[PDB]
Length: 177
Length: 217
Length: 12
Length: 180
Ligand SMILES: *[C@@H]1O[C@H](CO)[C@@H](O)[C@H](O)[C@H]1NC(C)=O
Image (cartoon, rainbow over all chains, first blue to last red; front, side, top):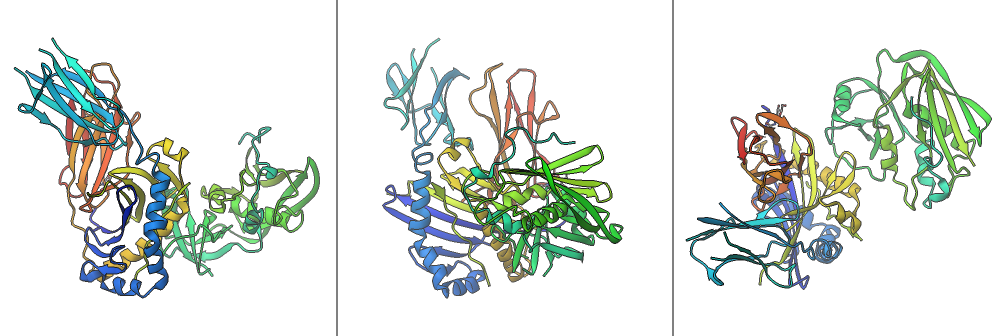
C-alpha cells in the first residue's frame, strides 16, 4: 500500500497491588505510538504527556462530569472488572506438563501452565545443578498458557523438578538411560 | 427456496418478557428514506454514512464487498433505523442494508405488491404495499407490511403482542424466504441485533413478489 | 456479572 | 512490593483502513475482543463467557470517539503518519514434538506497527488452512503490537513449515521456518 497510516490508540489501564488494596488507573491516549495525554488516578486530572495533548488536557479538565467519572474509575471500572474476572483470570491455575528428553544435553520441557510464576530445577543424584543449566525464559503461548524449557549440560538419575502455584507439591520427572 | 418454519423454530412472544414497544418502534411511522443520495463517508469499512434529515445515517452491510459497491453510487435508502446502539463519527441514527441503486430502478408510477395475512391460518386481511422501484429490498417491503399490521392488526403493542408467533414470507416464483417477526426470548430485545438480518441488502423484483404473513394467536 | 468499558474521552 | 496484576482495555483505530479494535488484556493475555461487524464479544477462552458478559455495543462507542480523535490528532500533527516498525517473527510448538502426536505450531509476530499484517502458513511450500487460528492484535507496553498464529499439525519427518509474514515495515515477505 502506498497510502500512509494514521493510528489512534487508547489504553485504559488498571494496576492492582495486594489484591485490590491499592489500585491505580490510567487513561492514556497515543498518537501513533507516542502518548500525548493521560489521566492518572494519583494525579486526579488529565496531564499533557507531550505538547500535542495540551488542548485535550485543558479541555477534559474543564469537565466536572468527565473528571468525576474518571476519578470514580478506580472503583467502578478497575475494582469492578477485577471482581468480574477474578475467578477465571486472577484465580486461573493450570498445572504444567513436564517432559524430560535428550537433545550430552538434557531438556526439561514444562508446558501448558498458568500463571507464569514457576520454578524449574535440575537435580543430579539428588543434588541441584546451577552451572550448565540454561533456560528459555517464560514463554506466553498466547492462550492463557505458558511454556518454559530448561536445558542441562550433562556429564545417574537426572530429575527435573517443577514448583507451580497450581500444585500442592513439586512435580518431579526422573530420567535415566 | 427456504425451508418454511419448523414446529418450534419461530419465536413465541409469550417467552419474551421485555417491552414489545422496542420492536414496535422499528415498524412505526418513523424510518429512513433517502431518495437520490450518495454516501458522505464511513466509520468502519463495512458501513456507509449518509446525510439524510437525525442528520446522519450509518448503513451497515454484511461485508465490505457490499459497502464498496454502494460507496460512490447514487442510491435510494430505505430502512428501519434505531438510535440506541447507534455509534459512529463522521443527530445520529443507524440501520442495516436497505440500499438500492437509484438509476434504472425507478418506475413511472407506484407498483402494488399483494400481502396475504393469515391469522391462525385464516386469511382475514389482504392489502397492497406500494413501491416505485424495480428491485426493492425485502427490508422495505417488510417494513411497509409490518407497519401496516401495527397500525391495523395491532401487531406489536407496548408490553406484548396479541400474537404468539408470526413470520413474513416473500414468494417470488418458485423461490421464497421468510423472516421471524417475533423477538428472541428473554427480558431484553436487541434492536441492533434484530435489524442485522437486513445487512444482506437482499432485494426482490417488485413485479414478481407476493407477500404472505403467517400469524398465530 | 459484567465487564465494564471505560469511555474514551472525546477531543477538541 | 510491585503490581501483581494489570488489566488493560486497549483499543485502536487506523486510517485509511477504517478498522479498529477493542480488547481487554490481563497480564499479557486477551480476555476478549469485540467483533465490530457481528457486534459480538469474542472471549479468548470460551469458558470465560460462562462467568462474565460484556456489552459489545459499548465497544463501538469508544471506537467512534477514537476515530474522531484520530482526525483531530492527524490534523494537529500536521499529517505526520506512522513509521513502520517491522515484526520479529518466531515459530515454536505448543509442546515438545513427537512423531504422530498432535501439536500446534505457533507463529509469534512481535513488536510491530501499524497493526496490519498478512500471515500465511506454508507446508512444503503450499499454503495450509485446516484448523488455523489467530489472535487479535495484542498491545505491548512500548505501544507496538503482538500477534499469535496457530496451525494445528501432526509432526512428521516428511513436512517442513514456514510462517510467511507480510508487513509494510518489511521489504520482502518474512519467512520463519520449522522442521522436525
Ligand atoms: C496483504 O495482501 C494484500 C494483497 O493481497 C496487500 O495488497 C496488502 O498490502 C498486504 N498487507 C500487508 C501488510 O502488506
